[PDB]
Image (cartoon, coloured by chain):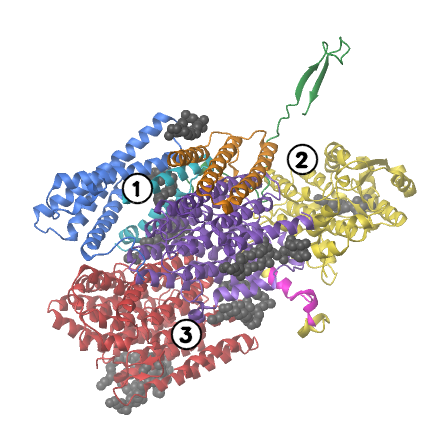
Amino acid sequence: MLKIILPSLMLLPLTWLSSPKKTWTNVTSYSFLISLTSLTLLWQTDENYKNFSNMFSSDPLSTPLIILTAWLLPLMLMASQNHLKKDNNVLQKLYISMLISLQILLIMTFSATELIMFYILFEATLIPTLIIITRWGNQTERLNAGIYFLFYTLIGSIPLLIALILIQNHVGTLNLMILSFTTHTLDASWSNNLLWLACMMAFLIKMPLYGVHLWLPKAHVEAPIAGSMILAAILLKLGSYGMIRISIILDPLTKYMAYPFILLSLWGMIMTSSICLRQTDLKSLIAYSSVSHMALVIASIMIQTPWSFMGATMLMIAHGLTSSLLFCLANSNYERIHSRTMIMARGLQMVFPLMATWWLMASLANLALPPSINLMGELFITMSLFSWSNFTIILMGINIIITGMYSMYMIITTQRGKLTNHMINLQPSHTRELTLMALHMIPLILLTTSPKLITGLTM
Amino acid sequence: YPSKETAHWKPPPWNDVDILKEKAVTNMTLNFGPQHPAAHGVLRLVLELSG
Amino acid sequence: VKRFFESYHEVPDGTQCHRKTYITTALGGICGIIGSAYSVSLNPADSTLEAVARVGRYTFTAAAIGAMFGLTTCVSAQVREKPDDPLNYFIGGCAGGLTLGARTHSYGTAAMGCVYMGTAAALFKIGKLEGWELFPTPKV
Amino acid sequence: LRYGLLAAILGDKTTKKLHEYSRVITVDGNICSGKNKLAKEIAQQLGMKHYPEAGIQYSSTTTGDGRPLDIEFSGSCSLEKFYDDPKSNDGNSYRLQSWLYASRLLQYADALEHLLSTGQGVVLERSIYSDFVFLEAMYNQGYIRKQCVDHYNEIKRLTLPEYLPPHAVIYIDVPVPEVQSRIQKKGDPHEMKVTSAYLQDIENAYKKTFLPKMSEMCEVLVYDSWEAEDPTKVVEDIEYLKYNKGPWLKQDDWTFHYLRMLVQDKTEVLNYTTIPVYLPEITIGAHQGSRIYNSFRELPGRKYAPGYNAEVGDKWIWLK
Amino acid sequence: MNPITLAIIYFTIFLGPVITMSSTNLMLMWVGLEFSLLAIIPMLINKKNPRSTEAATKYFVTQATASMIILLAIVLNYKQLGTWMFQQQTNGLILNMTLMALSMKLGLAPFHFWLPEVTQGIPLHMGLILLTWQKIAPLSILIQIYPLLNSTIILMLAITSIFMGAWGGLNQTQMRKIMAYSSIAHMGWMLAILPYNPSLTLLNLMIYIILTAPMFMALMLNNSMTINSISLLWNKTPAMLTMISLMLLSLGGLPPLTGFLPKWIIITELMKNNCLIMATLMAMMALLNLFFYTRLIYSTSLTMFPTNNNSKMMTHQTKTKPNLMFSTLAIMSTMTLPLAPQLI
Amino acid sequence: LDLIWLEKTIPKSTSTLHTNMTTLTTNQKGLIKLYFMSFLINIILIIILYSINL
Amino acid sequence: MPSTFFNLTMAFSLSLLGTLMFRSHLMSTLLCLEGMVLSLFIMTSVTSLNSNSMSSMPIPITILVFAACEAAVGLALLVKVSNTYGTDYVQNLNLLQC
Ligand SMILES: CCCCCCCCCCCCO[C@@H]1O[C@H](CO)[C@@H](O[C@H]2O[C@H](CO)[C@@H](O)[C@H](O)[C@H]2O)[C@H](O)[C@H]1O
Ligand SMILES: CCCCCCCCCCCCO[C@@H]1O[C@H](CO)[C@@H](O[C@H]2O[C@H](CO)[C@@H](O)[C@H](O)[C@H]2O)[C@H](O)[C@H]1O
């Protein structure tokens, strides 16, 4: 794994030593090459997960997330090349450094073997994210958004640290493989219930859960494009990954401790898909769609079945690509008209015919058009929940209808109708922007072609 | 965070020196004489002394 | 002595209401006394009569909160047979918080006190059941 | 070996260097009074160092290349704009006055450092003690606001009490009609716009607040114009002035040491002129401030520390 | 001050804690405490303004009363055991009195009120000395008697200190007061683990000092004694913003930075000793500190407050103040988590 | 629910609680008289604690 | 011995109470500190004499030496307070509330 980690570190001296003209070219090219290198994790020809040392590992669940993290960084650098067009060279290099440091920390987090190291890195990722949001946002509410994002995570994370310390005291180790192989049942005492809550709360907040999601729309609305990209793509999946990892030692309490959160997620998916129907900010609409989609991942991981885990992983990857694509599409119009209101710009397909094609593809992936991996994950989560209880199909169907409605409403409002002719500043779409959308879409098509890569541990 | 009680406060001076009210100096007043051995018996020297 | 307080855990919860209510009222009154002492010390009253009035207010409010907590916990654990269930303490803590809010004439304080005090009382009951110790001695 | 406690212990004591003409002499007077000529002659005859009146560009001339800088770097103020539109709306009046007070404070620090380090006296034209006359004239004429006056008074209260006053003050008294006639004769297209009320306010301040105050602690010498001419007479008065007054008598080596330490760090000298009092006339704003700061740091001989700019010929950087 | 006085007072300041740390006799430990108390007052009242005199008087009265209580404990132990040292058979009330008096000297809540005021009233370098060097002597005595201290008393003091520091730091716009409340919080953490593992108390002391000294040095760089004053750093000295941000976040205790290790290891040891409730409460309330540090970071490094016209003259000048120690201590305080096992 | 009650119940309520505690705790008059009265109360409390704990 | 030591302990406690509860004069608090020192000195002297521990007789004198140094420093601070405000009332010493 060090063969992936170390070049990522060397990107930083490259950024700070490259000439001001060539810095973006060099950093983007070498980030692409590191993303290519990260594909060596897909060479698994047996059921024996990869264990490189005492400190790093890779499984079918970790490898897709690691590869997605490696792949995103070039895309974030490309997306950040325009709104950082006026900043000083030192400031541009600082932004590049923040993004690279986020990539390094996320890869280390997803390759971590110990829960305590996982915790240290999963909480270290906050500093670059707070810096990116607050130092490069455009509105006065970015400070409060950053405060929310930081403390929603910290409050839930402290109990996680306490629980990890308790587990290490009781067992003697936090190594995930040792915990999995020597796992034993938990007595249904009140103390063990509180341990379950302390183990799951940090990840549920990060997911986020329905009741504690207010930090996510704020962060997306106030964050720069790279901030929104990385956030939606990976920082939400940190919670799902942690839940999948740590639930192996919390059995059998899950069977009865999952009801409150299964219900919260199942209802909140509907309650946020509905908000998407009448959200005025496009970024807020995308954020609430993400909340509703992550409700499915929460529910599937809670019910814990071979189908639920695979569907959750596939949906994690598919959402990571699709939400980032939607955020980039929205930012393309934002960089031109300087407003996030959806009604402000209309009929944009009359002036950006190909950007409209990217819009349509992103929206179709969002509403889950077969055979897209979006629909693979959603369908298998639906089947697992149906096996759980046959009345979950009612909520799933309501959410499906609402998802179709708001997804197509976005397109009809923005790309269709009569052009808002008064906008003289609608410049032709940049080659950079079109390449960004293409790089978001092509991996989705290839993974639809070969979905075996993005199944999880179970299948 | 202002409070009803803290309302009457003010920020401290930029350099710790405060503009403090002038201090009255009340030098002691003594009627040296007339009935004094060294006043020559008919001199009322009113002395303002500091110590 | 102080064993009067440790007498709270003699008969199983849900029995000896009057006695448990007396104990909890004493605890609340003691806490209110200490709080009034600190408030009068730092933040002095304008007059001695005003200071004594504030001491009385704090002590009576705290005693009422404690009495309500104890009475509601016992009454719950008696009306429903559950003699050792943290929900009784949660209900008692919410009743104490509502008492605080009513005495202060504040709905927001009522609700926040209910939630916080209920959680604290439930955790205290869970600690007594599961054997946690506040202030453990060094065992290493 | 920069000056410090170690240097003071090993030597470099001020009282040792002080001599008969190790004084501070401050020439004062209304606009166009002969201050420049009088100060130049006094300095040349007494061996002291002449310090031309601090202006908008004193700091730029004293630091870096020595060349004047763009006004955006040197204060965003203009004396010509002050005279053209004294009652502006961008606060050029008070911005100019505060900048000039800061420049005068910096120059006074330089003069005190020179005197204490070498023992050679300094002849200054006006100073931080007499700067307030212009502000009072501005306020009386309505060019600034009471808040600006309060801010100026606060900065003066924070900064002035830390330095010793001048040994001798020399006030050239010339009446307002002659000030006006001299201004017209000089013929400055902008200076000529000064009203006579403004000059009368300056004279009123000089004669009401300044001279009585400075008489408490310094040696004051008031001259008419016909005596200010022929500077040899003024020098002959100074040469026999007896200084038995003021705070200069109670000083000793271990008071001059700390005064020198204060006056030697120009950053500490100007620390309090930049207090965060959000007066609109002086507040810049983040965008313009960052733009100007970056443009300044991009100037030749200003990107790095003085000894570390290879563009301006600095050498041996890798071993410094 | 002239050189003779400077030498003779700095030597006394240095000698006090050295005598306390090296003494075997409780009376000579008290003598070291008295040396510190007497020698520091002139440096507190050096500048001679009403606030300086008030701070000096408050410090003197509080610390003299605390020293008298400590001497009472010492004398009663001498009466009881015929020895000048606390033994296993020393009386519980004697040890409790000693603990309370030493906590008053340190500034642990509720004996904390004097500390923020005295810190506010004195120059920044004196505040650095007071909050760093003066804490060693009182803590050494406690570390010598750690098998004898009362866990209940110490944990009440510790949690009270954490809560009061966290809540005090929120309401302060004054940098010296914020430093004082940070001191109170970190001293609460230090005292929480004294009965269990004084090595971790020493570790927390060392990390706290290595974080606090650079913060005070950075404050002294421009005499930034207020949030608005420090906000002008982006104009007056931009290069220090990154290190100030990292030092503040480390003081708060964010994982990747070195300041995390004290809290993490202390929670580990408390849990090992089965101190779950107190450990959880402390770690939970140590987030208000992160909040009021992040507010400072917003005001100083992640935004740009309005600046003054006169600051251009500031920009013109050349500066030489930051020592070689600032960089060393800041790097050591922020980037040392990987070397965690060596520190413990 | 999303813009009103879920704001009031969790983030706004927590922020209000701690902003109330900070103002309650940091309104000190700055008088050594009151500070030492508080210290006396603390000493009495500790003595009582020890006495009743034996 | 026992009754004497109990009385000395109670006298020290009274002096400590007089120190803790102020009464508008800094000099009176300084005097209460002196009273505490005196009580402690008597206790140590009585204990040493009763034990015949002659080697511990230096300690009472050192107590007085350091108490006298502390009293001198306190009196100097009183001089400074009187210079600043005109009296030694502790009510004035409240500038650091803000
Ligand atoms: C389930 C456990 C996990 C959930 C934990 C929730 C903890 C979150 C705490 C985050 C604190 C947010 O703190 C936030 O501070 C900002 C300052 O920017 C306040 O900001 C707001 O304050 C008030 C409204 O109340 C307005 O007057 C002000 O203009 C506005 O900015 C918010 O009212 C407060 O909510
Ligand atoms: C469960 C334990 C967790 C504890 C820690 C969780 C973090 C909580 C942070 C508490 C502090 C939040 O601090 C928050 O600051 C903002 C401004 O910044 C205040 O915001 C304030 O705005 C203005 C004044 O500026 C007032 O009119 C308003 O009423 C007030 O809300 C909030 O009232 C305060 O709550």
- Chain F's colour is cyan
SS under mark 2: helix
Give the image location of residue D229, x and y in percent.
90, 41
Of all chains, the one bearing label 2 is D
User: Among the chains, which one is purple?
Assistant: E
Q: Which residue is mark 2?
A: D140
Amino acid type of the residue that numbered disc 1 sits on in the rendered structure? Ser
Q: Which residue is mark 1?
A: F51
Locate residue E97 relative to residue D76 in the image: left or right.
left
User: Among the chains, which one is orange?
Assistant: G
Between the C-alphas of marks 2 and 3, the distance is: 63 Å
Q: Confirm whether circles 2 and 1 share one chain.
A: no
Residue D307 magenta:
yes
- Chain C's colour is blue
Question: What is the magenta range?
Answer: D292-310
Amino acid type of the residue that numbered disc 2 sits on in the rendered structure? Asn
Q: Which residue is mark 3?
A: A103
Looking at the picture, tell me which residue is in the foreground, A190 or F51. Answer: F51
Give the image location of residue C6, x and y in percent.
20, 45
Q: Confirm whether circles 2 and 3 share one chain.
A: no
Give the image location of residue A22, x and y in percent.
54, 78
